Image (tube, rainbow over all chains, first blue to last red; front, side, top):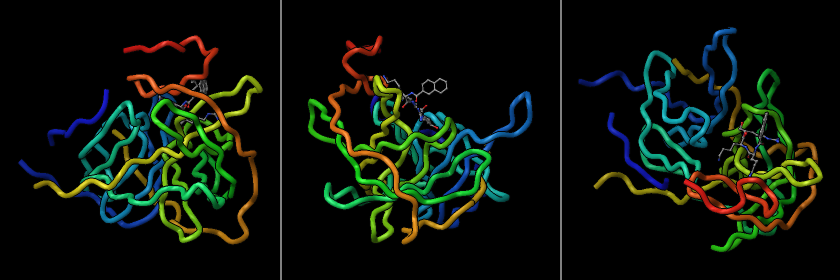
Length: 173
Length: 47
Ligand SMILES: *C(=O)[C@H](CCCNC(=N)N)NC(=O)[C@H](CCCCN)NC(=O)[C@H](CCCCN)NC(=O)c1ccc2ccccc2c1
């Protein structure tokens, strides 16, 4: 389940103002936060499981999924994956926590690693509630190095999320 | 039926709270995008 380019009579493209966003939805009990994401270079990035590819409304416009991978658990709207930085495996990083029902706050942490058969992946020991996935993680220069939301629950009950990230994709050729 | 609302700038906060330990964990990533610890029920591939 890795990689796929979506199929999206035009529509008005939604607001892609740079920043961190809350992904909202309406349920049988009212509106709530499904997840979060980060808008950069006119493209919306988030984990795959937050919207599962659902079209998103932003302003008076709409944003359609462009690319996504369930295995990578990443998804972007409006264009190719734009994030192009990753943890240097040395410095501390900061998560812009977009927790449902609470104001955004930054928490810094020294990443550890997930040892994969294919190498190592930065991993932050931060435990935040369902719906926080998509929250961006940044380095000291303020660049988005990855996303929060996909990891493991250790036997001690503490949650550890990998710094979910992919490489920048080129524009369609 | 899903929308988004901007809620913050993208930036490093000098006075940000500190939390968490740096761990070294062995895992596997299945085709469904699930990380697996050795003793998790789902440890052992899956589609
Ligand atoms: C995104 O908002 C969400 C944040 C989870 C934070 N969890 C935590 N602090 N403990 N992300 C997930 O729930 C994420 C979805 C993964 C989808 C497939 N890529 N879940 C996990 O990373 C983790 C996996 C654990 C098993 C690994 N083999 N699960 C959970 O954190 C979790 C499981 C079950 C339940 C049940 C009820 C409420 C919450 C949870 C969380």
